[PDB]
Image (tube, rainbow, N blue to C red; front, side, top):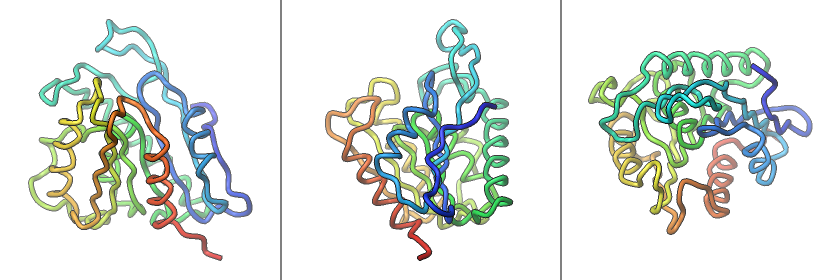
Length: 223
């Protein structure tokens, strides 16, 4: 658990954005992206995932929040790893709360499997968070969530989900399927789905403008 890549608050952190990178990456690249759209009062924490064998690619080691066994909505999933990773994130959120940033001033999000982890954690934590930015991701362990509203703190959480229509790794179909299930677990009045023409398993600058909009609207300065 090395030091995350952090864009700190200029003065005192009154909100925080915890963002988790995709497969095989570190937090450094995304911290830079969030540095380019930061608000002075917001702390941007991009932790680094541990290197580990990934079943999908002949157990070649690379940074990974959990194991990837497949790429289909029907693929087998690493249930234990997903749940332990989620525990680690809630642990990381608890730390930021005991250090001065209330949970309802914290946004969780990520890219690909980082986003998937973001959705799973937000929807299973009794910690009330400010929102979720789920980029080019999916809902892990769909069939374990009941078919009604989740209840709990994040019944009414705001979710911004973004996907490219040319994504070869997480098909747009899989994101569309994820938002439909989302709209049955939380209040769909706060569920926004954003599609980006031509984007692949990537980000674009408009997607980052819409993420800034989302964060700035939900985490405004206290002063």
